[PDB]
Image 1 (cartoon, rainbow, N blue to C red):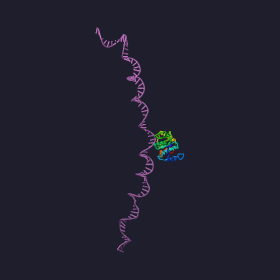
Image 2 (image 1 turned 90 degrees about the horizontal axis):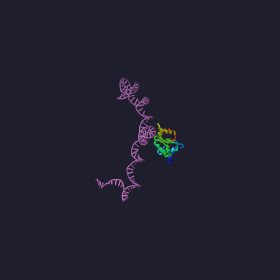
Image 3 (image 1 turned 45 degrees about the vertical axis):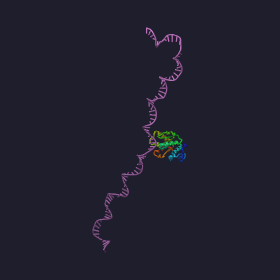
Image 4 (image 1 turned 180 degrees about the vertical axis):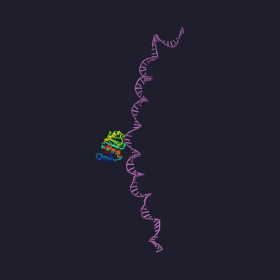
Length: 155
DNA sequence: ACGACCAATTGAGCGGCCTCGGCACCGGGATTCTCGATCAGCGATGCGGAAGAGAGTGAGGACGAACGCGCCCCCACCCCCTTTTATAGCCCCCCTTC
């Protein structure tokens, strides 16, 4: 996390409660959009320091997350990839991945190119799995993502 | 004096069987209409499969270029103009004879 990032007390409390010890605890953090939930997610990734997967409910959110990661973290643009049907960044070429539940949770036949990344995603283990707007997660298709992706801790 | 009782009379009202079946209430009957699930709806997402917009390069355009030839100029420099005289044949214009 670049020192430009400013962390508010409630944000710090939520992170301290999530990182009660040297081991990250899985669970849900409820913060308003104006409260900078994105920064907490980025901070958690910077804390875990391991390969992480961010999933948004829309392509607009995926764009927002990319901007926020660049805005708040030392990570370079090439190190971030937005695995999406509409756009390609050679996800296998970098460690940080961003996508959507509609893509990974997709029930119908995958495109040959998207299948390449998904198999790489399936085989790799994710240290942190950030889920945005998790109120949608209990959906029958979206919850499948949790069985498809292998993640050590999910926030 | 009449009031109740007694008798003979009798037949309407009554107590009852008869029977029953119209209706309602009561309860118990396969039920015309209930609810509890499925699928459909509105407006959104995303993915996956489809078209068009930009490209290339055939080629011939216009025409810049490169050359020779061409007309033309400004330029050295050279010769001729003019004068004198001797000298002669050569030549034309004119006069002159026939």
